[PDB]
Image (tube, rainbow, N blue to C red; front, side, top):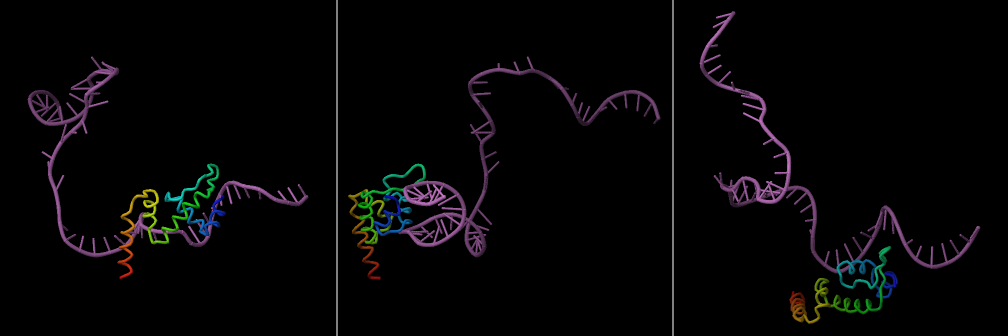
Length: 90
DNA sequence: CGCCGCGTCAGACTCGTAGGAATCTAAACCCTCCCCTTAGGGGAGGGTCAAGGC
């Protein structure tokens, strides 16, 4: 699935997928070496689902690039919770 | 104007590897300019992919 079809699946911008492939989170399955076309798979839909689930929780993207591969990191969730509590009280 | 001692200037072998020279040293202010930070958006410029139309 090309980047337009996949972007239509997730209801997200093509620029979002470009940015994500740039920062390393959600790199596509197959990069066509001739023209650079990004092709995607449902395994990328499953990675993007949790990416969006964490993004909807307020985690910054560089927090996500640590949270989704170093799965055992647990202090960053009570940390984000105390940070949101301080922001809400303010 | 001529000659004599003095000031000055210019020259002085080709192969390998080692192989350089090593001291000394304002600070507190202000300014502009350039790049940087999210999480991507927007566009320009340039390519690429299947459709067919003759």
